[PDB]
Image (cartoon, coloured by chain):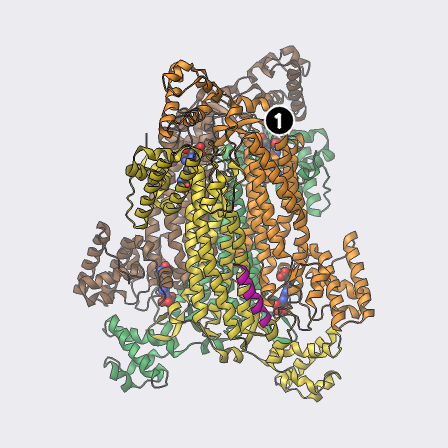
Chain colours: A brown, B green, C orange, D yellow
Amino acid sequence: TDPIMEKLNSSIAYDQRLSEVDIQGSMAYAKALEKAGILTKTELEKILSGLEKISEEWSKGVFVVKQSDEDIHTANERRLKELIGDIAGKLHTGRSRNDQVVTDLKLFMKNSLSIISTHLLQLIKTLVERAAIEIDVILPGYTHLQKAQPIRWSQFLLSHAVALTRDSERLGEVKKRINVLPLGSGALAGNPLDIDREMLRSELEFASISLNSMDAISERDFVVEFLSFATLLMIHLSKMAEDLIIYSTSEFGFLTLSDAFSTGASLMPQKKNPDSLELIRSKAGRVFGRLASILMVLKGLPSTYNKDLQEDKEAVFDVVDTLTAVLQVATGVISTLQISKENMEKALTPEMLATDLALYLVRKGVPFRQAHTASGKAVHLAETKGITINKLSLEDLKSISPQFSSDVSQVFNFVNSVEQYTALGGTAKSSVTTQIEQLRELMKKQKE
Amino acid sequence: TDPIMEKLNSSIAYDQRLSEVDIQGSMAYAKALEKAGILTKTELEKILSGLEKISEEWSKGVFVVKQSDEDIHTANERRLKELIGDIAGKLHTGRSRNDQVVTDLKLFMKNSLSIISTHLLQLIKTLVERAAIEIDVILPGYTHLQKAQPIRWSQFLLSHAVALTRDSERLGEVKKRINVLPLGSGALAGNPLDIDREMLRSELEFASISLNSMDAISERDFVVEFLSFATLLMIHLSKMAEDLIIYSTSEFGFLTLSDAFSTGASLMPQKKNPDSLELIRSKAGRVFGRLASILMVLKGLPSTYNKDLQEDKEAVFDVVDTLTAVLQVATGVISTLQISKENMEKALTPEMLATDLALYLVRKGVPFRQAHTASGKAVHLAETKGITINKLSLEDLKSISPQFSSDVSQVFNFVNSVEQYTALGGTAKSSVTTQIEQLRELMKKQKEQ
Amino acid sequence: STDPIMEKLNSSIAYDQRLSEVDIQGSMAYAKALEKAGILTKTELEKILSGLEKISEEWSKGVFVVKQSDEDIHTANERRLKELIGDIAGKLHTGRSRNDQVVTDLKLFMKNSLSIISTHLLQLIKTLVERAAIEIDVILPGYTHLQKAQPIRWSQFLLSHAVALTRDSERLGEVKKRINVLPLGSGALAGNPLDIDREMLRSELEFASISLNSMDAISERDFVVEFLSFATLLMIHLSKMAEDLIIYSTSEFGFLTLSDAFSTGASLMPQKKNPDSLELIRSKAGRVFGRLASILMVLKGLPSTYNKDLQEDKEAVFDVVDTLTAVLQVATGVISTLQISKENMEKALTPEMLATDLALYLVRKGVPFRQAHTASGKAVHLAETKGITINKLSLEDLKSISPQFSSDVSQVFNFVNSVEQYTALGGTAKSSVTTQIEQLRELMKKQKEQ
Amino acid sequence: STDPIMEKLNSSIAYDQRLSEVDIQGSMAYAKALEKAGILTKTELEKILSGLEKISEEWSKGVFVVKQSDEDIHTANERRLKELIGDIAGKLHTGRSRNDQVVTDLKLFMKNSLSIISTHLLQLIKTLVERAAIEIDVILPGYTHLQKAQPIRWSQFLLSHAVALTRDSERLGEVKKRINVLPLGSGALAGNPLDIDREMLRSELEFASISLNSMDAISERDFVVEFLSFATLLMIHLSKMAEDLIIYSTSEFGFLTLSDAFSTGASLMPQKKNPDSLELIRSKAGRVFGRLASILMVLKGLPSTYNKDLQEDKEAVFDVVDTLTAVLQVATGVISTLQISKENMEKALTPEMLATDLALYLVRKGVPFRQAHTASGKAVHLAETKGITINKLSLEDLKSISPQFSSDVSQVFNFVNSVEQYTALGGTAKSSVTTQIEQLRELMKKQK
Ligand SMILES: N/C(=N\CCC[C@H](N)C(=O)O)NC(CC(=O)O)C(=O)O
Ligand SMILES: N/C(=N\CCC[C@H](N)C(=O)O)NC(CC(=O)O)C(=O)O
Ligand SMILES: N/C(=N\CCC[C@H](N)C(=O)O)NC(CC(=O)O)C(=O)O
Ligand SMILES: N/C(=N\CCC[C@H](N)C(=O)O)NC(CC(=O)O)C(=O)O
């Protein structure tokens, strides 16, 4: 026996995290075994009693792993034998580590996903609640990281909330396919003892049962799917982080993170580094790496079970802990950051209203092309005079288009600017208000 | 201006494919602009007529792209001006290339997903039909690419069909989020003219409208998703390809692909190369590469629109054409390959029944650990006598365990072996029939949706 | 029988046509080799080489007509040859396989492309170095966590990107080395069966050496993968420079303005310039990485030797070669034509950024690290309480904090003095920047030669 | 003003403590440079070096106690140093940053690791080449599309993998050289402010040269990326070799059997061995590639200079270093102890595989390529008709097809003669194989 081979093959170091679900799966299997008459009533009692002790050992942190333990399945089996004797061996009857390992992982994932959902909905709720409070705040909207047009700060917050809501929906879709029992698939051909799979389903609380035994022990669709959901969520978080890091620069000055989510030097007490957001942004790569690895692991693999499949667990574990930490830090950052209403409003410039000046002519019937040419001229005329467009005289304006009336004065108002956007989904207050309502309802349906 | 910059920035070369959907998007927008008062009834008639003429030029292949057209959106508006004059310019009022391009890509992807769905469901149907017909065929089931135990050829075919059915379910989920109208989001803050977005939705036949203008124009979730669906689908096909390429070796000898899906030489007329399956398997890399690229493009990008987002189209086009081609070739391969029932059956060996021999004792009350011990003794006994286990004598077996009775001869039958797995999902004939029924019911639902 | 979708998917002619000229060059060399092996006559050789020339010429002019039967470039070029000189043409492929012919084609193509990519990369690096030399006096904030950390020379910023790009150039040279090995003569997988003169082929095609093992030479796509790895790391460097430049071009930072040629805008906001050029560059990091990811997946788990899977290499190489070629030139245009705002870079320098220098001032007078740092922190607090900035504290103010503070301390509050502290090799001190420029010109020279 | 999730997420101590020793070496070299600069007196230096050595030993003995306040390995070492020698410890970080300290620690560790990896890699290559020498007489089928194409020597196959591995070894040397550049003395980003003697730090730490630009030296992770690229392409090679051997080990091919140490089996089927070793190896290509993917995404689009995002480099490097070390050794074991079936390999050789040589026979006689080819096809065609193998055709039968067929055609139908055709450099002919073995031995020598 080669020690390097043994260490490489062995999965106990990390798969012991599945200790509890593994016992849960065995208890369920033991009850079906009895029903199938493989075990006597008394034998069942003994088995279940022993399994409960083991759950407790792991639970209290007293379980002692042994050098011989290849995986969590062998470890639990070894300890039950130690606790109740020979009778423990009837438990693996008609059972394979192949369907046992995917049953364990799916039960762990269903529980993990339930937790991730709570944190994801909390992040969304936090953004939506903040959008509701700061709905009167206006700042520049950007394209190419250049000032485009005024937008409400809440529109920006809600843009991230909406995208995250789609991540929550995908999470639900992933959870559905994970909530399918694979136990009773045996090594690849199914269970040979006509085990009551419906009974196993009910006991382990799965929603339905796997359709084909070969597919059940061979596929890791649920792992890839979860990693795809995870990666896109991180993409969203990498973008929100990017936005917030830039807005927190001294140059932008739109906001400041709380002390808990930033770092800084006593020599420059006014400066705060957004470490929280940089950690979050870098995890998009950490999680994407996991998705890439499993995809490459599964590609070109022959049916059915192959040891290549063992690489699934460490990837799922890393991403579950990554998502759980990242979502809570994101929530914290969003709920505690402080905005500078003053600097956001200060960033609004008259130049950003030339588009609105053109729209003014459009609403009066001037064709789009000529309205844009007119505004461009007003902008040019102001520039030649060394003044801003909101300062041009009505006479100056008419020298370019008699269509400009004294009411053109209303164009140079940033509230009036964002208020143009009443069509559904836009930045006008009535629209932002509607979005908050839709999101509250969406979160409700998702939580449910 | 810099020529190389202009070439790199211009998207006309490929976004040309969006010609029809772009025209369809402008027609719906034109209709809403008229209802909004930006266009007169007559102007709307002139614009829709001109737009219809451009649609025909593209379909007929006579559209003339000018050196000045930077993108499909520009080419179409230029042409509309050539056709109807000045009024053509009012078309873009309140619209932006930002909400126009994602509307175009979504309309295009919605149509492509319908076509892909059709070929995906056809592949699944083909595998299911063959499993129904060849339901008596039995062969080795593998683990570590080593013979593990008997299974029905149909169980193998259905394992691939079940996976593909999950792919079809994901396709639907992706299609749902793609079927959301982004038009009327403007450059980023919304449409400034109170365009009737419900009307645009109904005209373009989208299921609902986008919730937030900034997100509608900035996100490419729908591209990523589609690419994740495509990639997992390809993973499944590369696995089925791996299986069939191996099963097609002369060493395995289980099956032979038709001439249409293989290649060969006259010097060796009996040898066939599965080029079709190798093309398919390598397309998993091709598709995954598009997924990785778009994810990297979006990572770390600030809000809202950035030119980085232009990389979406070539990746979507490639994957759509890869899937449509790959799915039809896969269906072809599955329906036209020829299996060797004789070699598949010859592949089944006695050695593969030692587990069964152990279950035989188990079903008689013998504890798992000791039934396996007894079956082991049996194997060794036959081993030291130069004979296969099914040739071991009744008294021989008895010397090992008295619980071995005359009825043990039924263990040495491969049909009885697979018939052990009647538990839902197993390889027993009844289970296979149930699966066929389940998938058919599943396909019915996915199709009526 | 034949399936239209299958033959369409298997056919590579639509893209492998690009290898037309190099496919013909490899045939001219193999022909010459066949003649030496005694397979062709001196008379035939002249015929064949004469026909290949016409073919080679037809592609060059753009008059070659591909036919429905042409499944790939190898088949197309042969078809036309037979059409040009007759049955004698059919002897050219004697002992040759599409297996060793296609890899020979791709490497010759990549050798030429890499030489072109080298020129562009070296020009980008030279652009950054020469600009650094000219603007060596410009000082602006150095950033960490995108927060102002400390004064640095703008040329130090330019050279940081130049140095990274230099390592990309070095990698390109290593990749080209392995690409510059002849695979022709490996046959289908067991080698050339006619005892062809591989050295003659090497010489004729101008490869540096020949492949050591037939199976490997036929199935490996290492040269494609590392070309792609090199391309991907190069794009990463460019994505970072793009990010910096995009942020520095914001009106918030106001450090620089791209030229109109490499940006977009509207007459409605004439002063605003969108950095489309840099955005295209940043996004191509994804595009190129996607190619590396695809080929690695195509090769993973493949059995020996040739398999049709390998056909996916060509489209990935073509895309990346064309992407780098366009991207590097656009990058060079961006760097050489952008305008910096010395005024704004200078205005971003604040007294608060010298608190670390203030501590260092004490460290050089023997004050321990902890005490000096504490001392500076106290000055920062005193300044704030007094309603001023640290460069405004009086000597008495400073002495009340530490006895080591002497009148010369006023020299700390000078940004040139600040960057001039970093004379240790690699720092932002003017002499260090000068040295780097000289080292980079040297490196470019040696790489240029290599 | 502190958040437990944020703290846990931000600290790197859990994993960067692996850099405990090289961190100490970096501190010792720095301390010496400081003494030379005059920042430390010789006496202070002797006390600092003495404390650093004790910390080095504590880690060596697994006695080092990490405290909850330890954010990273740099912080934990500085804390303990002060506990051991008092205030004097504070002068050590003078003019230094964790920014140039961490990359120095990572390059030192990676240089040591690449040294170990090269040894195992060179040993894997040697294993293949020496086996090829010994089994040089063995012949078996060569495959294209996994279909029998033409006879080749077993040694040609083995050497094909050795040659690819040899390029991996070359890339490793290239990567090591760029890793062997000292970044210490770069400070936070602008360089070292105390005119520290970098050439001295270089000599003490044994780097080949020193970094050229402080910002780049602190910001770049090229060294991490290209080492992950080297590792990923190396894993691709191993995945390819694993695929070949897993297939050759099938009952269906019967070409070889793995030893018990690197295989797994079933008790009811003692003659069957599962190549778990090779599957673990194949799957690791995905695991390593995942690491490559993650770091690329982490770096993509990041602004200069240091960002907390860069913290993700370490876990990826450690995982891959440990993966290659184990994988290379297992691969060596599998190749060294596996047993081939000369009988089965020769058995797989068939007359059908010689039609090609028959055509070559005519071309050497002077028959134009296409004629020789068409003639060979007629030969196989007629053999089939008469329902006999091609080696059974009478010279008469052959002459009717082509006048150029002489009695010596009998030479074509021999497998050794078949492989012997390939004497051109690189071919499978015994002489060509011998030349390869010699070339590879010299290569391995030079790569040292
Ligand atoms: N070892 C095994 N399955 C192990 C599952 C748990 C494993 N650690 C994993 O994570 O995949 N199975 C087989 C083959 C079986 O598939 O028939 C064998 O005994 O070699
Ligand atoms: N050009 C543009 N979006 C173009 C979309 C179509 C493009 N080919 C793509 O594929 O993304 N937008 C802006 C900035 C706007 O976003 O405010 C501009 O005019 O510079
Ligand atoms: N099809 C082939 N080589 C094709 C090379 C060019 C191809 N378009 C590619 O790009 O890989 N070879 C074989 C098998 C040979 O590998 O022995 C055959 O069909 O006979
Ligand atoms: N935290 C930091 N460097 C940390 C290095 C080690 C870290 N665990 C990593 O792995 O990147 N730097 C700064 C900013 C400095 O870069 O100016 C700070 O003190 O906030």
Q: Tell me the chief SS of the magenta region.
A: helix
Q: Is residue B119 visible?
A: no
**Label 1 residue near ligand 2, CB within 8 Å:** no
Extent of the magenta region: D434-448
Q: Amino acid at mark 1?
A: Ile
Q: Is residue A317 above or below residue D35?
A: below
Q: Is residue B1 visible?
A: yes
Name the residue carrying label 1: B38
Q: Quadrant of residue C48?
A: bottom right
Q: Is residue A444 above or below residue B255?
A: above
Closest to the observer, A263 or C172: C172
Q: Quadrant of ligand 4?
A: top left
Tell me which residue sits at (41%, 36%) in the image. Answer: D35
Task: Return the residue found at the far front.
Answer: D42
Q: Chain of mark 1?
A: B
Q: Picture coordinates of residue A159 (x, y %)?
A: 47, 33
Tell me which residue sits at (39%, 15%) in the image. Answer: C397
Residue D440 lies within the magenta run: yes
Q: Is residue C368 above or below residue D219?
A: above
